Image (cartoon, rainbow over all chains, first blue to last red; front, top):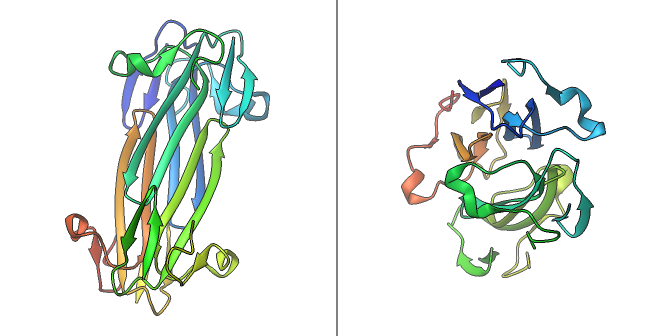
Length: 57
Length: 57
Length: 57
Length: 57
């Protein structure tokens, strides 16, 4: 599996079967962006995971 | 597998075979702490993962 | 003005008239802790700011 | 003073005399972007602060 990871495409470890992408703003001037390979999402974050190459663009 | 996750103990998803704990300070007044279940660590973060119950305390 | 800043006590710059302390969980495994000298808070966070020495313990 | 703040232009509080913009990667999958009005920078980050309208694009 390959995933986007902040400007590059990376090959996942064999135990990471998903790509992930999520973002949040804890404060109006601070953005946090999570993006890369991952294991399964929580159910509440089900749509933040996908499992095909480069799907988390 | 069970891991600490910021004050609680959680049961990992079956595809998460590790517990993880890492911290960083991007600025002197900001601490980020990552703690919970995970998949395998990067080699550069090898000692941030462990694979026994509650090992990431 | 002096403020706590992650285990230490620091002297604020003269244009920073507040101390600040807040914590949150942008993601379930990620804890953010913001503590130290500060300029004025947003209106809704006015109680996270204080203006007396070491008030942000 | 007016500053960029993640896609918008905002007016600073009167005690915030600077605009700020910086980004970093605390962890390989985590990008942090800090942009908006600010008090004075740390000495080593003096070039991340500026004091003219919209200077932090």
